[PDB]
Image (cartoon, rainbow, N blue to C red; front, side, top):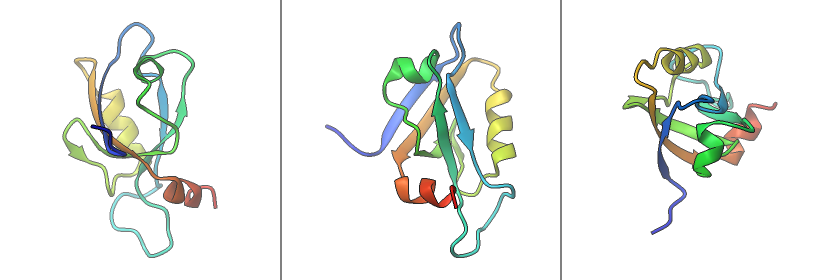
Length: 105
C-alpha cells in the first residue's frame, strides 16, 4: 500500500508544474563514480508538485511521460518538460539521497 516508488501525475494548472530538476551535462552512459540520472532539485512554493505532496527534492525521476530518463542529460529532461503541450506530466519517482549527494561533489 505504500512504496518508495511513487507514480505521480501532475497537471500544469494555473501556477505550473512547480518543481526544478537537475541532471548531468552529457546524456548517455556514465563512468564509475560520476553522477547520473535526473533529479528533483527544488519544490516551488506554488504549483502542481507541492499540491500533490508526493514529489520531493532529492527524488530521482526514473521516467517522465513514458520516457526512460536513466541516462538523460539535464538539457534533454528540461526540454522534455518545456515541450509538453497538453499540460500533463506522469512521473516515476523514488528518493535517492546517495546519488543526489554525489551531484553535490
